[PDB]
Image 1 (spheres, rainbow over the protein chains, first blue to last red):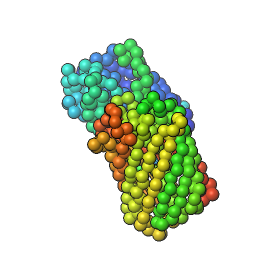
Image 2 (image 1 turned 120 degrees about the vertical axis):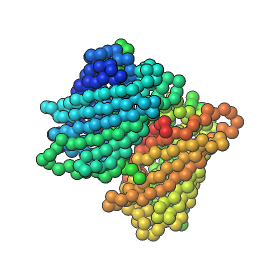
Image 3 (image 1 turned 135 degrees about the vertical axis):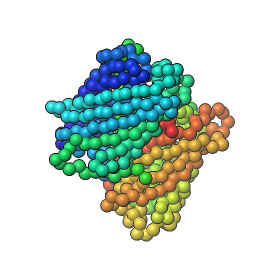
Image 4 (image 1 turned 30 degrees about the horizontal axis):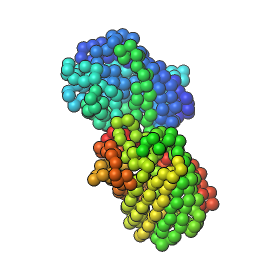
Length: 220
Length: 219
């Protein structure tokens, strides 16, 4: 499992969804250093572009294999290979928008392949998401809890708004390994510090480059 | 102030004190990238070595100028130059050890100068600190609160112990500018993520090299 995840790994993503009835499809390709916790993704909106909502609400749906885990924290995600893992997430914005995401992670001839589906509903028409008045996510900390051979993650995320305030968004995620034959060494409770940054964008946010640093740490 | 702090800065330190009655003195020199939040220091125990306690309890006393503050979080420390700043810290270990630390930070001939005094008492004789069974600090988050011209920092630190457990330690720190006349833009409440790594040691921890990465963030 860990053996199959090299110090350098490429990744590819297909993401399809509907937000407030607007249907789209994105493709992404990138690479990272799974044991250093760093990755970069170049993303294209190939159907439904330009999107009438902030790409920021999609950005967190495009990579758990790339978390730096110190020796003392068993790495559920790297141990899941070769079979990979799935995750399901609910994002609840303080102003009432909701996003549900299902993701499949697989390893296909040494490339990490992500397949994702997104449904967004009830974003206020005049709110910062549908008015495209957002400016990226603040750094955040996700609490990880073992739950019967899977993991649950919870985080309060803060979407920056034009003018300097934030839209708060609760994330709840269930992570499940696809492994059935081998065993996984389960972690106890821990935290993951995440920093997701946009590097560049062009053509009304139909091309986006983003980079994430994510590091697992002891929780007190 | 920020203009005096260059993209690369060297630092020198003198730290002296007593822990459970044991008297010692340390000198250090290093350099880092203050806007990138990275720094490295080479430390010698020049008096009282070898120490009969874990060097880890001194490691966090040896550099606030080297914290990456992103554009929206005003940098109290870099703004305090040329006068610089002071800090006073109480470290309370859950097994009863207490340390008071008093530090002065100044700038001389393009070099950051650190002068620190440490007084540690009531470390258990067969605890991990006095038995030298510690293995570094876990990465941690310090909460920073504005207060009456200064900043107060709060963090629960976790010292790794031989065999895989942790000894917890409360840090409360008061940070005060020596720029007592002149405008500083005050931050609101924020957090600093710290990672302090030992790189090298020799001669029973009387030579230590350590590297720190520190990054301020929204709270």
